[PDB]
Length: 269
Image (cartoon, rainbow, N blue to C red; front, side, top):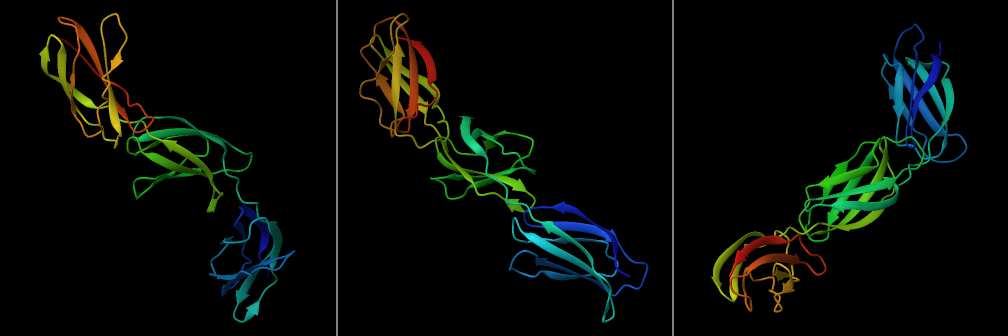
């Protein structure tokens, strides 16, 4: 007796799954084949235990028509095949209009557009041009945005976004993005004179290319410390200032076009 009530439970772009009801009998096991019906490719044929009533044939060709026979075995003897035909799905499509929404040193968030097909989530391969080890991440199907955490500051990343549907991964959408630079820290006022201030700070995590220091009188535009400190300096003497004047200092980082947030403070000459 052949199995009955054959039904396909899940069809992916690479697999097909089905249940059924075993014919009340002895159980030597089952045989199951899947042959391209309208083409020439494999010929997946897999055996199954005697107590089976479901199956999962994976690793099939995308967008392909398959004949599926489900044979019940009993000692060299075979029974009539429960049949059906399934056509695999076309692989999943990569996300569209992938743009960066913002970044905060160690994290970058992005938003993309979804095609209209059965999805089971996303995956993000974030690769830094600097570092030598990337961070892989997975996402949930119901969201169209995601902040990537765990990056370095001021580092440039090649971010690959993918779509997921079971063991099916789409081709990627590539996105160039970089991190915010971490502002210098602990601005300390070492010395003063009616015409100058000596300031020291903690260098950023990034591997900046120098700083720009700004000072402004209380009713006059901020000026840059002309000489512009080399990235190797961590202290600078601000000269040519007015006496008894309360100045505001801004120490900012640079990695060739990226101004870090500004490190601030005030002190009077």
